[PDB]
Every structure is written in structure tokens, then in C-alpha cells.
Amino acid sequence: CERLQPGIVQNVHIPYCMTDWGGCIIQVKKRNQIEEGWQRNFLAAILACSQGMRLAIAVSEDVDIYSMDDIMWCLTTRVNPQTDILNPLPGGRGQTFMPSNTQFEGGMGIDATVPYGYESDFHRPVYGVDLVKPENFFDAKDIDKMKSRMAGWVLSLARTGR
Amino acid sequence: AERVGEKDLRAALEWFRSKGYLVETNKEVNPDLEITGLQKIFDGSLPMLFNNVKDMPHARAITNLFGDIRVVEELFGWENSLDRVKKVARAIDHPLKPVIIGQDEAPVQEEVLTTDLDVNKWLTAIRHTPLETEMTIGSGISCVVGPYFDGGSHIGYNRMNFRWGNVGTFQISPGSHMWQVMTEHYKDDEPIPLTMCFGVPPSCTYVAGAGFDYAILPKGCDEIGIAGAIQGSPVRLVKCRTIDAYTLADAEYVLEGYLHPRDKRYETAESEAADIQGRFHFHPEWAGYMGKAYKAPTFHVTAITMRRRESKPIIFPLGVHTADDANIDTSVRESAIFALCERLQPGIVQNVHIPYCMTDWGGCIIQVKKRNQIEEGWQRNFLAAILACSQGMRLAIAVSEDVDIYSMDDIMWCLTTRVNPQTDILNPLPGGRGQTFMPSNTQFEGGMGIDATVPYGYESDFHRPVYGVDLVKPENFFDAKDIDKMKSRMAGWVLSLARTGR
Amino acid sequence: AERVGEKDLRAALEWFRSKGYLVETNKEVNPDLEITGLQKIFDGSLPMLFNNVKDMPHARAITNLFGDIRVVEELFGWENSLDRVKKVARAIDHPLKPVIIGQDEAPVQEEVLTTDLDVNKWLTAIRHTPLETEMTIGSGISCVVGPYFDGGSHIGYNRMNFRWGNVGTFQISPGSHMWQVMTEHYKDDEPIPLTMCFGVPPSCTYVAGAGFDYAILPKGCDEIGIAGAIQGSPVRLVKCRTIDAYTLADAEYVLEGYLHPRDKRYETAESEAADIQGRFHFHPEWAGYMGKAYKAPTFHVTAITMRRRESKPIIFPLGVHTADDANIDTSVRESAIFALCERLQPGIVQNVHIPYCMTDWGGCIIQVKKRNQIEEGWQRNFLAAILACSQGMRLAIAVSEDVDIYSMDDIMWCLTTRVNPQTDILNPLPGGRGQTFMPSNTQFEGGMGIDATVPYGYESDFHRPVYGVDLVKPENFFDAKDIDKMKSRMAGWVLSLARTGR
Ligand SMILES: [Fe+3]
Ligand SMILES: [Fe+3]
Ligand SMILES: [Fe+3]
Ligand SMILES: [Fe+3]
Ligand SMILES: [Fe+3]
Ligand SMILES: [Fe+3]
Ligand SMILES: [Fe+3]
Ligand SMILES: [Fe+3]
Ligand SMILES: [K+]
Ligand SMILES: [K+]
């Protein structure tokens, strides 16, 4: 992605849950109007140059790329099911382990990014987690009792305030 | 001398003190950007009680009450989330008839105010994000009992903005239960009398978030009938002092008055100066975005009835991108989707989960089990029926029985491996009715039904292998210092995979 | 001496004699190819009563009882088909509790036979088409009351073929109410006791045809509760003499016994010699095709209880491609689709019509009315919800309010003019569950939701102009000889267009 157009893709994460060569998540940042639409060129190039990728997801810069509940939040809210799902190579070469054309269905490029210029309509609001301090209200026994029940998406959302 | 509720918020607060789940403080918290700021730090955690609220000498504030779902399930006597879904959907089909008590026995009618009705003097308005301009009351559920709901009852949250004293805006989402009352009585000369209740019993907080499941709970159903059947005792109602309606008797604050559908005003002042709709911020919305201000109808308060101010009545302010708002809105909706799938063909759907990450009405995950060849393909009938009967669902995912439905990395594993992108993606209603908050046909794109299930008979090719996590014991190899050092670095998908051995 | 039913078939036959709607004869009709042959000649017409049936010295036969819908609506006190749909859907939500009378007061238990149970000796089997090989009993509805239907009740038709004396086949369509009882108690060692009733009251004939509408009438509902609420009086039940179940007391013949789900036999002899399924004819089916013979479960009759043979008890044989079979199967299904659309968003759908030409469960036509901009697009939510909650619907059409919903040339006019072929054709569930009779996914193609409605705000461009058929009078220009000569050549779309002036 830095070879094709540099400065757009900020982070690439492949987790445990997308197997070895099953999928990937990239994170793009659109600086202007010309760079809008470059992430669809990235998802077609990732799914073609990697053999047997089935799920390439492009997300925007305000997403935690390691929190996997944040990726499902972008699939719910930022995905048009008619336009933002790519099937670039239907009948190409996939992987025969994981169940003029073959039986490979094509892969899935999912554009969960925001459009450029519509960032104000899609802006995630930030709560005041830095304007208040929890040490002024509770003692340290009550903080560690309350912080020990937090797991999953709430550890990522309490850090960013999102 | 003093009246006591049956299963109200004060009895639930004493139960949290016995189990050690209640965290209290006496420092003066701010309603401006400190209640929801502390709620976001401790999202999905223990209930926090604020005894001292700034410029609120009689009000107490509870927050994060529905944060952890393990203490909501311990409150109502449920073992897990699978026992929670199957018992509320049992309680939907058998509602309990609510009782009506006298006006001298209702604890919410201890202090009845009929003049100088300043609602911001008595009810606590909060501010969520620092980009807001206005202070928003959003702690009240709307109790409509009687002939305006066809002999049934309705409870559900509505946000307010009191800017003209006793008159404030009343935001109704379109297609809801309050929208169906308002479109029926739009051209009526008489106003609609309703009652907004604050500091409700937590069974009535539970059914308050149920909405857009109207094939199961239609207009004319008993929404406080389900709240009676969840707690096991019928909810006490009482007649209003001024208007001809009914309240919830075991609440803390009750607003009585009339709703004017034709009288519409702007929610914010800066959207009232520039008279447009849909671009100016009010507070955040249910999607994790900002809601915008619109031309909401007006609720004209005629009376404020409230408990005794020396006993310090409790309000429940909550943020909208919190796990309170997830576990209120999506908890009966897990059961109502499970009730719809058991209505269509029973015995197939095992579990329905709606997490925090699929917003309120954004999506759902169901879990099916195909017993034979005839039941194969029934999950595509379920995903089309879920996406049509729930207004504004965008992502319904059906998974098989060998998937952890609560681990969200396990759902992404089914999207990678078990989904054909040509056949297993459903777009059932392209151009139908969606939700206008979350961005002969409309602009709605249709929703997405994703069939991540295995085919019947191909279960051996799609079987997840199980490692021997029960054939070996780690206590025979390492000491207990080395186990807890090694178990403390495990988070995410590896906690689910080490339990099942998958 | 003699027991009298409340609202049974004998009381309905006396009401048809008073209005002149009953046509009787004393010639000996044949059950082989003469009852259904005379039913097809007079399809959609007056009820025909056969006093003498060949090789049936105690049986009387009524046919074409539900043929004309204008005399079904006159029987139950309904003005038209719009009043029929809105009152049965009212009666779905308020069922009447059926009463239980004693065994000495039930008229169907006058003659109880427990030995030499030859069902073809007493119950009339008919043959529809000349390509058949076997004689089929298909006049009985299946009454399951009690713990096998979760405290509710179920009535519905099932075909039989008694070939082994008291043992005959019992065809259950998959996904039905009897299929859900059978899949629950498939591995049970005890058999399922049910009761097949013949010569039922016509309110119980009316709800018998209701099926695959299980979001409205699920398992555990009261299907004889709706039959009590249609006729206005509760249906009398009585305990069986041998088995532990309940019958309908005001019937003419009742078969009592047990259903064996694991014991399965072939329906025909020629499909039993060559042991395949799905190619050999049994009788025609509901689609207007032939049904094929399969491996049906067996109903083991233990007792035959019947009225007194000198009083000549009445059976109701009917063809399956007749207007009896259309107006039995699609009449509560018109109301249940109307109940589902009023559950989702009320006030939009005005009328639901399922004609003869869309078979039983093949299709439906709804009629919507868009009041404002918010209600635009709600009919695509309706067509996706109708096609998913009804199993095996293939053609759901939504039309606007200026269409005659009963004139079928007016529906083809909306397919020509108001349908975009790119946007207004819905395929909601491609690969789901359909019907195997009518020819991770199945072979079902998905159904077809057709949006033939106008957009909101474009009603002036799509307005049908109205000619002046009321501003002129034809009696001022022609005599009454010339009017009735000119009006007798009008049939089809021109009868609907001359009434509305359209
Ligand atoms: Fe990695
Ligand atoms: Fe996108
Ligand atoms: Fe409601
Ligand atoms: Fe939830
Ligand atoms: Fe699949
Ligand atoms: Fe039934
Ligand atoms: Fe019909
Ligand atoms: Fe159209
Ligand atoms: K609600
Ligand atoms: K039926």
C-alpha cells in the first residue's frame, strides 16, 4: 500500500481471528478529495496479490484496529451493502484447505471507511474522560473493584473516551 | 408516615449494598460533563451512586446501574445470558396484570406540586459531550396506560429539553410506539395525556428499552405487563392528581401533563436561530454518532409529583454510548427476536445475542442448529424476518452451534471462513424503512443478512477440532505462582478458546 | 332422545334453505369422479347437497359450501370482504375460550364404535381425477387440544388413505403446526393422541385452512379460540371415550386414536411396489398440479364415534383446485397477513386479498396507503415480512389505494405501468425455505416482492382519471330493453371500470 500510493495507509493489522491467510484489516486516512477512493484500489490489490485472502476490511483513522468489537461497529454503521462490498476476482485462485474459472468465490473487500468531506456527519463523539479524575471521588479500593469488571470493548472505549 | 415501594429502585440499591456491588461517594459531582465522564471511564461496571449533585440539593444520582450484565442477571435471578433470553421471552407471552393502588398509598405522590413548575429546578439535566450547547433531561420513561394505547400499556424513554419553564420538547423516534399514538391522534382537538416517570423500578427500566420489535409487542400490548412478569410481582399504578392517566407508583419523580403533536419547537437555541433541521448537535445518539436537533413535539407539564425531599429521591442519568444504554435497549430485543424465531419454526434458534458493538437497533447475532435436511435453509427465513420486522436493523448474522456468540473475534472467524460472498449475503428490503439517525423507495440500503452457518451434512468438513485442554492438568507441571503469571496475559479470543479447547 | 348442536353444519344447512342457497338432490351420486366432477362444473357457486351417495347408505354429502364468498360472508354476518378481513383479524387477537360439555350431551357421541373399525365402511373416500389409483379420505380436520399443543388448540386438514383397515396414512406438510408437534415428540416412546373430526361447524372449517402464518398464530395459540370468536359462541368440546384428548362435540363423525411418527408407510400401492418418493400420483395438490405420494406417518384409529345413522350424518368432500379450497385456506390468511402489517406499522395497509388464482400459499396482494413522507417505503418492509413469515409464498404484490384489489386485470395494469423492473422487484430470501409441492441454501428461489405502488408526492402524475359515469344517466337516452341488452355483454375488467368510472 505504500508502494501504490504512500501516506494513506496508517496501520495494517491481521489478528488471530482472521486465521493466517484468511483476511486482513487496513486503516486508511484520506487527506484530500483526490485520495478519496484510493482504499478501493488497496482492497482490490491486497485480495489479488495475496493468494486466498477472503476478507479485506478498510477502516478509517478513528477506529481502534486491534479491538475487534470496533471492527464490527464499522460493519454495522459505515458499510453500504450495495456499493461498499467488493468481489474482485470471482473464480480465481483461493486456498484449497479452507472450504475458465475455479470454485473460489472471490474474496470480500469491505469499505468501512467514511467518505471524504462527510467526516463531520460520521464523527464519533468523545466523552470527558480526561476532564474528570476518579481519584477525587472514590478511594483506591473502589477504583480497583470497579476496574476489574471491565473487559472487551469497554477497555478500548474508556481509553479513547469514545 | 412513610410509604415503601415493592420492588423499586431503593430496594434494588439495598440489594447492591448487600452484595458489595454499590460504590457510593459524597463528593459534589457536576451534572455538566462529570456524570457521563465518570460513566465512560467505568463503562460496563458496578453501579455508582452520587449523593451530592451540583445545584441539586434534594436529588441523588445513580449511574452505571445496567453496566455489568452479570449483576443485572443476579438481580432478577438469572443464571446467564441464555437463561435471561429464554425467561423474558417466556414472560412476554405471559404478562402479569398491573394493580392500581390508592393515592394515599403511592410513594411517588408524597409531594405534589401544581404551581411554579420549573422542571430544571427539580429534575437533573446533564451534558454528555463538550460540543453540546444545551442541558438535556433524558432520564424519564413515558407511561401511557389506557385508551390511548388500546387498553394496553407502554413504557419507553424519550429525551427532553425544558427551555420554556414547564414546556419542553419531546423527541419521538419515527415508527415507534409513541409515534403510533401520535399519528392516530394528530388531528384530534384534545391533547394526549401522558406521564413521564423518573427513578423507576429496574424491571420497568428493562422493558423501557424494548422497541422496534412490534411483531411481538404491538400497539395494544401490555409493556408494564412484561415488567410485572420479570420481577415476579405486579407493578403498582396510581391515578394522576390532575390529568386522567396512570403513573408508576414506585418511582421517584413523576411529571404529569399533556403532549401537543401539532405544537412543534426546536430542541436547541442555535438551531432555532437558523431554522434548519438535521445538522446542529444536541447530544450523541444511539449509534455512537451525534444526534441532531429537530422540530420535536412539546410536552406541557401540568403537575410535578415527587417523593419527600428529606428522603433524597434518586434520578438515573445515563450516557447513550455506554453499556447501560446497550443493556437497556438490547435486552428485551434479544428475547423478542428469539420469540419471533420460535414463533416461525421452534427448536432451531438456540441463542440470540445483541452486543454493545452493534449499537441499539443496528444489528443482531442469532445462533441456529440444523437438526435435519428439512430444517436446512430455515436460517435464511429467520434473517429476512428479523431484518423486516425490526425497523432499521442493518446487520443480522446467523452462526452455527459451535460458535461462541459472545466472543466477537469468533464472529469475525465465521465471516472469514463460513461466508460465501455471492450466496450468503442477503439484501432483503433495498429501499425500505431504515433509521434516519444512523447514516417508490427511500434512501435505506436494505440491511445485510449474513449466513455464516455451515450446511447440513457438511458438518464434518467444517468441524472445529478440539485440543486436549481437559486431558492435561497444568498444576502437575507448574506451581501456582507460574500459573497466575501466565494466565494474567490472556485477553480477548484466547480466553474463549482456552475454555472450549477450540 | 336427540341432541342438538349450537352452530353446527345442520344449523347452517337450515339457514341455506331459508335463503334459497341450498340445492339438494336425491339421485345416487358416485364418490368416484362424480362429486368433484360436479364441483368443478359449479365452481364458486351455491352449496350442493347429495342425499344418496353410492355404497354409502348412512352418509350424506355436502359440497361447494365455501364456494361463493358472498354466502360465507352472509352466514357469519359480514358485509363484504373488507369487513371479513378486519373482523377475523379482530377475532384473532381476542379468542373465545371453548367450553367442555359432558359425554351424554355431545351429539357426535351418539354411536360409538370401538370394534371392527373399518374407516372406509363409514367415512366416504373420493377420487378427484381419472389418473388416480387410490380412494382418498380428505374431509377431516385434526383437533389437537391440550399438552401436545402447549395448552392451546389446533385445527387443520390432513389427507388420509386407509389401506390396512383401521390404519391409514397421515400427510403432514413440513413446517406446519402438526409438523411442530411431530418433531417435538419424534423420539418419544408414547404415541401422539389426536382426533380427526368430520362434518364440523363452518367456523371450525374456516380456521382449519389457516396455516403458515405462525408469526400471528404460533404453536400454543388457540385455533378453536378463533373459531369461537368468529361465530360469536364458544365451540363445545368433549372428552374422547378411549384416548385422553378432546374432540369437537358438534361434528358428525369423529375418529379417535394415536399417531405414530416413526411408523411410516407409502400412500399408494404403486409407489409401495417401486419404493421411491415424489413421482407417483396420489390426487391433485393445492397448486393446481398433482401431488405425489410420499412416506407419510400412520394414524392408528382406536374408536369411531359418529351421530345416529337414521339422522344421516353429513360429510364434506371437496376438490383441491376448487373455490372451496381457495376460500378455506386463504381466508384467515388474508386476516393474518393484515394482522402482521397492522402489527408492524398500523394505518397503512387498507386491504389484503388472496384470490383463487394465487393458489393457497402461493401469493398475496396487499393494498397500502401512504399518508406522508415518513410512511413512504413502508410497503417494502411489508413485502419482505410477508414473504419471510409465510413459508412458501412466491408472489407478494403491493398496490396503491386507487386499485381494485379483486379485479385481476387491475393488478396486471399495475404490473405494466407502476413497476420499475430494476428497483421494484424484491428477492428477499434466495435459498430459504419454500414449498416442495410446487416446483448453506436450498433450491427455493426466494419469492417475489413486487412494489406496484406509486411514490408519495408523485400521486398527481400517477392519478387515474375518472370519466363522468355519475354526471350522465343512461335512462334518459335509452329504454330499459336497450340497457339490459347492452349491459349483458359486459364481463371482466369493464364491470370494475364502469363502476368506478376509471
Ligand atoms: Fe498478526
Ligand atoms: Fe463506507
Ligand atoms: Fe412501547
Ligand atoms: Fe445486549
Ligand atoms: Fe454459510
Ligand atoms: Fe394449526
Ligand atoms: Fe381468498
Ligand atoms: Fe412502484
Ligand atoms: K419500550
Ligand atoms: K389451520
Image (cartoon, coloured by chain):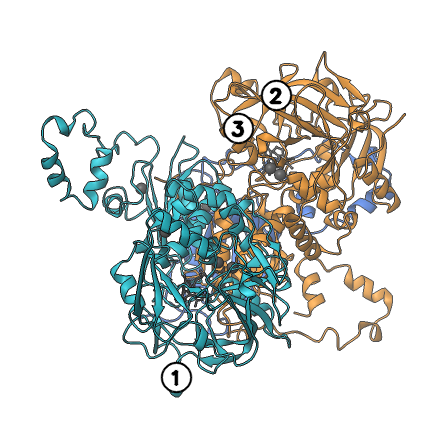
Chain colours: A blue, B orange, C cyan
Tags 1 and 3 on a common chain: no
Label 3 residue SS: helix
Furthest toward the top, the residue is B116
Question: Image quadrant for the C terminus of chain C?
Answer: top left
In the displayed structure, would residue B441 be above or below residue C109? above
Tags 2 and 3 on a common chain: yes
* Residue C447 drawn at (x, y percent): 37, 57
Which of the two residues, B190 or C59, is positioned nearer the viewer here?
Answer: C59
Label 1 residue SS: loop
The amino acid marked with disc number 2 is: Tyr
**Residue position marked by numbered label 3 in the rendering:** B182
Which of the two residues, B127 or C271, is positioned nearer the viewer here?
Answer: C271
**Mark 2 or 1: the one toward you:** 1
Chain at numbered mark 3: B
Is residue C114 at least partly visible in the picture?
A: yes
Q: Residue at x 43, y 60 (%)?
A: B421
**Residue position marked by numbered label 1 in the rendering:** C269
The alpha-carbon separation of the residues under discs 1 and 3 comes to 63 Å
The amino acid marked with disc number 3 is: Met
In the displayed structure, would residue C456 be above or below residue C274? above
Tags 2 and 1 on a common chain: no
| Crowd around label 1: few <14 · some 14–19 · many ≥20 (10 Å) | some
**Residue position marked by numbered label 2 in the rendering:** B258
